[PDB]
Image (spheres, coloured by chain):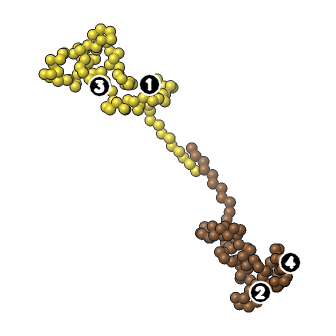
Chain colours: A brown, B yellow
Amino acid sequence: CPGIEMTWSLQNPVIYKDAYQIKHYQDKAYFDVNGLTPERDECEEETGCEPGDLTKRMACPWQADFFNCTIQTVNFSEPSVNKASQTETVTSR
Amino acid sequence: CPGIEMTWSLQNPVIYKDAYQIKHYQDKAYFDVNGLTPERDECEEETGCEPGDLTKRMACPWQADFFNCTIQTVNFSEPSVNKASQTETVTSR
């Protein structure tokens, strides 16, 4: 959520050519001529990974993901709620 | 209230021999033989002053009358009341 080094793209088997082996999208020549594809999702198109696809989902800069990798205060009464709006009224005499 | 240098015993004419001049109780040859009377009031006795009578009514030590010599947040609604008891009760929901 996302995690530290990588995220849930590493869970999709569409990224692999075999167990532990990443699928490689296009060749050096294709990149020398056209560069990288920015909008492309290696999960949508099952044709492999382009350089930078395994880390692109992580925070920019990474210190955000490290900053939030601490502790969460989780709701455990309402299955579909994590966070809500709270309203505190203090009336004194 | 009592003051800085002297107190209200200086408004009593009974300690004066004549104007501006203080009345002297006994003489030199009394304090060498008997010592000084601590109990004696110069305003009540009417018979003159002993060494110490003029500043004895002041704070022990003096820095008290000086520390208190600042300001006063004086009540102006009730002539017989200077200080009273206050109760602040705070009820909050």
The alpha-carbon separation of the residues under discs 1 and 2 comes to 96 Å
Tell me which label, 4 or 2, sits earlier in the chain.
2
The alpha-carbon separation of the residues under discs 4 and 2 comes to 20 Å
Q: Quadrant of residue A57?
A: bottom right
- Label 2: which secondary element: loop
Whether discs 1 and 2 lie on one chain: the answer is no
Closest to the observer: B28 or B24? B28
Q: What residue does disc 1 label? A: B80
Task: Tell me, yes or no, whether the two marked residues, 1 and 4, touch with CB atoms within 8 Å.
Answer: no
Task: Report x, y in % for residue A7.
Answer: 70, 77
Q: Quadrant of residue B57?
A: top left
Side of A4 relative to B52 (left or right): right
Side of B80 relative to A13 (left or right): left
The quadrant in which the N terminus of chain B is found is: top left
How packed mark 4 is, by other alpha carbons closer than 10 Å (few <14, some 14-19, many 20 or more), is few
Mark 3 vs mark 2: give the one in front: 2
The alpha-carbon separation of the residues under discs 1 and 4 comes to 97 Å
Q: Amino acid at mark 1?
A: Ser
Task: Report x, y in % for residue A49.
Answer: 78, 82
Relative to B78, residue B26 above or below: above
> For residue B56, which numbered disc appears in the image?
3
Q: What residue does disc 4 label? A: A34
Q: Amino acid at mark 2?
A: Lys
At a point 48% along the width and 25% down the height, the residue shown is: B78
Read off the chain for label 2. A
Q: Amino acid at mark 4?
A: Asn
